Image: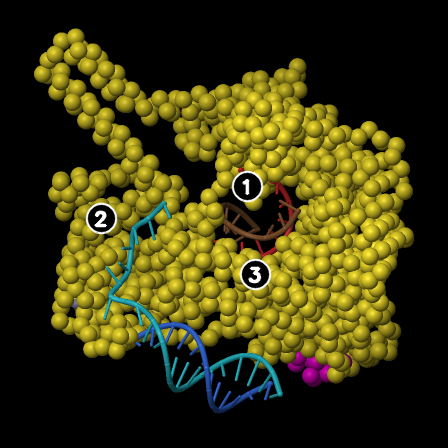
Chain colours: A yellow, B cyan, C brown, D blue, E red
DNA sequence: AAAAAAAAAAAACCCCCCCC
DNA sequence: AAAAAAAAAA
DNA sequence: TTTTTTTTTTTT
RNA sequence: UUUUUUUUUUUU
């Protein structure tokens, strides 16, 4: 049984103080010149583990001190009673037993209420309790049955432990010593080398700010490594650990020796879903490293990541910042189209299936590759130290098995591991690209040979008979030195031939399996013919979504919870499918998706709140419903940003087949329109993007052909017969947009740099540029304030958050007219609300409470969610519109909520409570039903308590919507007390105790004043806060 | 000629919280 | 410019 | 009574 | 029960 630090122990004030004192004392006591900082760090970790154990034991003893004392007294009295019976001793025994039962019940209620508060704070939000609600129950890691090496089925713990340990030891023990072959392979193919500045940046001394940033960036609530220390320990005590972490990291920089804790890793085996649990090869292993080792590796990972752009070619998008996966996907699809359009088909797209690449990459080859790339000095020394003695131990069924060395393979669970693996695989990628005998596919002017995402490689080959054999030879040569072994039999490939005998010969000569219809790459079903891209990617997406909704048909959550479920599980899949294949989709797809989503959201019932209202912004109810058509439009138009930026690494944008206008996309956004050119006739992604961009620009009444962001090298200047040297000078000296040059009176007159640029340009180009820019039309079209759309697509040099910004802008643009239920409420109560009242009601809906159940109830009350007798009477085409519960009156929504004679007593009790709060709130239904207050009550010092009381009353009334009994004041007290308890424990957890007390003390006092002792006892109503 | 928006007509299912 | 959640891919 | 769907008209 | 990249949503 290993030791794991809990986050509850860290949050304790006394424990935190004692732990900080112990850390400071150890750092100022055991530091000397006879002990290295690595051994001192290991001793510090051990002492911290011991101190944490001692503090936890002390806390448990203190929490159980009363229980222990009462138990000892009870045992002594029982022994005395057995020795000699006495009535008074029996009375004492009974009293002690009653006190013990009361304390145990109080502790159980404490735990239950803490769990309930944690749940209710996230009841319907996009968070853990909802993700675990939709996800299938997690399979346990308790592996009791396995198939041994002799083919027998065994359940003996020793045999299964031995089998698993031996399998994972033999997996990581295949370390190669052929250094000469590694050197030969590295010298055979050219690799990039970092310059002096980048090497110095890598080898720069570590500073405190880097360690602080890495510690703050550590994800929370993550399983700790073998030492049991979580990231929360380092985040909470960073003010005391950062100096000693600096000392340790400088020591390891100078010496190249790491603490023994930096090597030990914990391997957890996950049973692969859909696979046999009795096979040793059907388990996914994951490695947990110590938090300090992860911090060091993350520092190194960031240091190498700041140069990974130069070290890694843009063909590899996995683990590379600023590179998205679909960069390859569309690219691959484009290649397929070019093959389908070729008159002579002699092509092959091979999906190379790497077999446990992370577990088979040779550490010596990785080190030699790092040395070859010019990475040397402190950084290389630290990396070599990391992989000098890596050791991992398997946690099987909660038991720590004997550790085995990681002789080969890259340490999983390491932040530096993905970048090192990319560096290693880049040698093979460049060898394939630099091999003249391995011919790629020529898409226009771009030769495409391979695309990469981590170890998932796709190779595009022309003339497969020779190209594929050369690729296999090169891959085998790379594997002989690096261990990057390929499961060829599992490498699905599309083979395009124009002759059956040629296809048969290629299949016979090559060991690659041939996929006739589809290949799964990055979760996308790439098709042999692009015309089936929909049929294999979006129709199966609809089928999967329908199956998921049918599985979630009886899920125990409300409509808000189901909307958040759609946003959490369904929305990312649809967004990813749109990003990978943004093709023109029929309205049938969107109609079916919307129908399925709406049926799931409303539990196969008719929508109580209009879809158009929820499709608006958060001001229209606070919940919002995902608009899939707007997300699709945003995804399609996103490519315009890459068009305008014109990155040299976005090769996918240059892979679109075309016969005319070879260079249009970089001259298409904020540029002169095409001169009646029928470009993109057979385009698959880009033409639809341009069409949607034009549609959005037309809807905005915007001119997208001459904007303030019109590039200097755009068609507007090139059509002036301006020499390319002048354009380059303008780009280098003034800026990138025509606004930087200036138009009208501002033409080359904004800066002395403009004077220099004018002096550096040929006079004819100056004359033509002045004629174009100083023209009235250009001046009025350029010198204008750009909108949010142009700013989104031009002013952002980074694509992070681009989809969200475009979607928000489209939702703002497509602000369809919707009915206002608050105005309907005003009509019901014979009142007129100003725009201030409407905004107040919307803000009350948005900010009703931290928990989502209270907000959902407030939204239901305000947005006319609840059904009324009038609605049912009209639906059933009958005159039985009399109000429910029996009053003989017409059952309007206002009457059922506020004006019912059987509901009036509850509101009168609420107003009596308000009077006891010294709040002269008028008996106005708008205040509780919509959150609309008169101008005389603009003070917010009492609005929180009033909101809690009103929402509790709304819950109580809704509970008895069609019951003949009146909404009971006791039920209202109980509901507001449940809210009080949940908010109390939430404020304790979230350190919001002061505001909670300020908003709940008077209400709690009024509650306790009007309740009898029996009611308080049987309803678990008792004081929870004091004078604090 | 095609797409988008607005208007009109038809249809539904007497509670509603609760439910990790 | 921070904190948290989830999902996608590997 | 409310929402969704279909049809018609208008604009590009 | 990891790590990296990217994405969305919510709270300022
Ligand atoms: Zn009534």
Measured as percent of width and height from the top left, residue A326 is found at 67, 58
Q: The residue tagged with tag 2: helix, strand or loop?
A: helix
Q: Does A451 appear above or below A828? A: above
Task: In this rendered view, identify the residue nearer to me: A871 or A303.
Answer: A871
Query: Is the residue indicated by label 3 positioned so its CB lies within 8 Å of ligand 1?
Result: no
Q: Which residues are magenta?
A: A772-782
Q: Chain of mark 1?
A: A
Say which residue label 2 marks: A974
Residue A941's place in the image compared with A663, above or below, is above
Q: Nearer the viewer, mark 3 or mark 2?
A: 3
Give percent across and percent down for residue A896: 21, 67
Q: Is residue A58 visible?
A: yes
Q: Give the spatial CA distance, label 3 vs label 2.
A: 46 Å
Between A592 and A567, the residue placed more toward the observer is A592
Which residue position holds label 3? Answer: A541
Task: Give the distance between the C-alpha atoms of the residues marked 3 and 1, in whole angstroms.
Answer: 32 Å
Q: Which residue is mark 1?
A: A219
Whether A695 is among the magenta residues is no
Query: Residue A206's spot in the image, x, y percent?
Result: 68, 35
Q: Is residue A925 left or right of residue A432?
A: left
Q: Residues within 10 Å of mark 3 (few under 14, many from 20)?
A: some
Q: Residue at x 80, y 39 (%)?
A: A479
Q: Is residue A18 above or below residue A999?
A: above
Dots 3, 2 in contact, CB < 8 A: no
Q: Nearer the viewer, residue A599 or A698?
A: A599
Q: Quadrant of residue A110?
A: top left
* First of labels 1, 2 by sequence position: 1
Q: Earlier in the sequence, mark 3 or mark 2?
A: 3
């Amino acid at each position: 049984t290993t030791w794991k630090l809990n986050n509850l122990l860290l949050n304790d004030y006394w424990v935190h103080n004692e732990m900080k004192a112990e850390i400071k004392m150890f750092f100022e006591t055991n530091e000397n010149k006879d002990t290295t900082y690595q051994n001192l760090w290991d001793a510090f970790k051990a002492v911290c583990r011991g101190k944490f154990i001692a503090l936890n034991a002390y806390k448990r003893k203190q929490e159980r001190s009363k229980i222990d004392t009462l138990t000892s007294q009870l045992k002594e009295l029982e022994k005395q009673e057995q020795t000699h019976s006495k009535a008074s001793r029996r009375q004492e025994i009974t009293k002690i037993r009653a006190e013990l039962k009361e304390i145990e019940t109080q502790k159980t209620l404490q735990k239950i209420n803490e769990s309930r508060s944690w749940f209710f704070e996230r009841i319907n939000k996009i968070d853990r309790p909802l993700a675990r609600l939709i996800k299938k129950k997690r399979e346990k890691n308790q592996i009791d049955t396995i198939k041994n090496d002799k083919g027998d089925i065994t359940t003996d713990p020793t045999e299964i432990q031995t089998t698993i340990r031996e399998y994972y030891k033999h997996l990581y023990a295949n370390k190669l010593e052929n250094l000469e072959e590694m050197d030969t392979f590295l010298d055979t193919y050219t690799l990039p080398r970092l310059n002096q500045e980048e090497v110095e940046s890598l080898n720069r001394p570590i500073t405190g700010s880097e360690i602080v940033a890495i510690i703050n960036s550590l994800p929370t609530k993550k399983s700790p490594g073998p030492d049991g220390f979580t990231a929360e320990f380092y985040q909470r005590y960073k003010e005391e650990l950062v100096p000693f972490l600096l000392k340790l990291f400088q020591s390891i920089e100078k010496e190249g020796i790491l603490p023994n804790s930096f090597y030990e890793a914990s391997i957890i085996l996950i049973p692969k879903p859909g696979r046999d649990t009795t096979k040793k090869e059907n388990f996914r292993p994951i490695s947990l490293m110590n938090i300090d080792a992860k911090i060091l590796n993350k520092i190194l990972a960031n240091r190498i990541q700041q140069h990974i752009k130069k070290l890694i070619h843009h063909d590899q998008v996995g683990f590379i910042p600023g590179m998205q996966g679909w960069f390859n996907i569309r690219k691959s699809i484009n290649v397929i189209q070019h093959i389908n359009r070729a008159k002579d088909k002699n092509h092959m797209i091979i999906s190379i299936d790497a077999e446990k690449a992370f577990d088979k990459i040779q550490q010596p080859f990785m080190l030699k590759t790092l040395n070859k790339l010019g990475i040397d000095g402190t950084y290389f020394k630290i990396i070599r130290a990391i992989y000098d003695k890596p050791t991992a131990n398997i946690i099987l069924n909660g038991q720590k098995l004997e550790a085995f060395p990681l002789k080969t393979g890259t340490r999983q669970g390491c932040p530096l591991s993905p970048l090192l693996f990319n560096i290693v695989l880049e040698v093979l990628a460049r060898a394939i690209r630099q091999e003249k005998e391995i011919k790629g596919i020529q898409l226009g002017k771009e030769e495409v040979k391979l695309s990469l995402f981590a170890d998932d490689m796709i190779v595009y080959l022309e003339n497969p008979i020779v190209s594929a054999q050369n690729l296999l030879k090169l891959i085998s040569n790379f594997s002989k030195v690096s261990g990057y072994k390929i499961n060829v039999q599992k490498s699905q490939a599309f083979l395009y031939t124009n002759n059956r005998q040629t296809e048969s010969q290629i299949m016979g000569e090559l060991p690659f399996t041939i996929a006739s219809k589809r290949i799964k790459y990055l979760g996308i079903q790439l098709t042999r013919d692009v015309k089936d891209l929909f049929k294999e990617n979006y129709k199966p997406l609809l089928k999967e979504i329908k199956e998921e909704t049918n599985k979630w048909k009886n899920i125990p959550c409300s409509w808000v919870g189901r909307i958040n479920i759609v946003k959490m599980a369904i929305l990312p899949k649809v967004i990813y499918r749109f990003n990978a294949i943004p093709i023109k989709l029929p309205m049938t797809f969107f109609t079916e998706l919307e129908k399925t989503t709406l049926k799931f959201i409303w539990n196969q019932k008719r929508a109580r709140i209009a879809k158009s209202i929820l499709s608006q912004k958060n001001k229209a109810g606070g919940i919002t419903l995902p608009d899939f058509k707007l997300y699709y439009k945003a995804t399609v138009t996103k490519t315009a940003w890459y068009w305008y930026q014109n990155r040299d690494i976005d090769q996918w944008n240059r892979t679109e087949p075309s016969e005319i206008m070879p260079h249009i996309y970089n001259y298409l956004i904020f540029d002169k329109p095409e001169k009646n050119k029928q470009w993109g006739k057979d385009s698959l992604f880009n033409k639809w993007c341009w069409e949607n961009w034009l549609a959005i620009c037309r809807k905005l009444k915007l001119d997208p052909f001459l904007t303030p962001y019109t590039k200097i090298n755009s068609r507007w200047i090139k059509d002036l017969n301006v020499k390319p040297k002048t354009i380059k000078t303008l780009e280098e000296n003034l800026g990138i947009t025509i606004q930087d040059i200036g138009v009208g009176k501002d033409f080359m007159s904004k800066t002395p740099k403009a004077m220099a640029t004018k002096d550096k340009i040929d006079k004819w180009d100056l004359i033509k540029l002045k004629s174009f820019c100083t023209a009235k039309e250009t001046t009025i079209r350029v010198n204008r304030q750009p909108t949010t759309w142009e700013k989104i697509f031009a002013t952002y040099s980074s694509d992070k958050g681009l989809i969200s910004r475009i979607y928000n802008e489209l939702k703002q643009i497509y602000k369809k007219k919707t009915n206002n239920p608050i105005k309907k409420w005003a009509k019901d109560m014979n009142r007129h609300f100003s725009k201030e009242d409407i905004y107040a009601a919307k803000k009350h809906m948005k900010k009703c409470s931290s928990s989502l159940a209270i907000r959902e109830m407030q939204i239901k009350t305000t947005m006319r969610y609840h059904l009324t007798p009038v609605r049912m009477a009209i639906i059933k085409k009958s005159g039985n519109n009399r109000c429910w519960r029996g009053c003989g009156e017409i059952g309007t929504l206002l009457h059922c909520w506020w004006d019912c004679k059987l509901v009036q007593p509850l509101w009168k009790s609420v107003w009596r409570f308000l009077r006891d709060l010294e709040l002269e709130i008028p008996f106005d239904p708008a205040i509780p039903l919509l959150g609309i207050y008169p101008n005389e009550y603009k003070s917010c010092c009492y609005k929180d308590t009033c909101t809690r009381m009103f929402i509790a009353a709304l819950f109580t009334i809704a509970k008895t919507w069609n019951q003949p009994k009146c909404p009971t004041m006791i039920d209202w007290i109980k509901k507001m007390w449940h809210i009080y308890t949940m908010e109390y424990y939430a404020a304790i957890k979230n350190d919001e105790f002061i505001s909670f007390v300020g908003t709940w003390m008077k209400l709690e006092t009024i509650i306790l004043s009007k309740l009898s002792q029996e009611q308080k006892t049987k309803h678990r109503i008792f004081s929870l806060i004091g004078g604090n």
